[PDB]
Image (tube, rainbow over all chains, first blue to last red; front, side, top):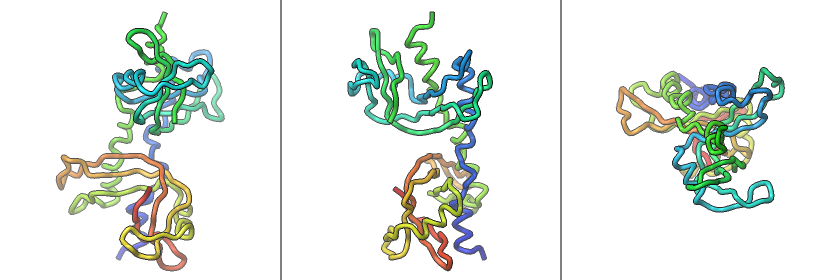
Length: 124
Length: 124
């Protein structure tokens, strides 16, 4: 007769930090997308949304870039994205990144005609 | 000379949903935790935090269980959890789940002494 408490563990506990699955995503993707050459780009974000949607962002809410010259845009709705941050022990040419899967709004700078993202500003 | 736009794609686009490594996590978990035996448990949540940590929620803020019980407690801090929900194609004995990773407060029901979680109520 399984105890109600033990039942809770079997059904709801998994401290083995699930997300581990893609723990080396940043490590791999940060290498293939040639962003570890010479030095390790400290921070980087990946948007797993449809290229169309990201592009449609250019026609959303206009906002300032964390710079000082207006040209950035924030998404109406949030998008699945992956955050890659250089880890502590990381050392070129053996970069090491931490992978974090989140869902926030994105802010990009657009340009050209038609307008397309040309710069990734930040998220939230 | 790579165009700035194209540079954006190389550096920030991975439209192919990077949650595949984890897009079948609930399927494995719902399986091994005996929640697909006899019938597919429709909804279920996994707390990706230390046990001891969760157990402390038993002594955090007090709350009203979704129904109306007086006990129950709500974690003061959010936690990494995963949401598993039976898909539309799911039909015993072929349980199929959708994996949703989120961070939020959980609501539990405690019991016995010392108090330990004996039931998962909800989250927000």
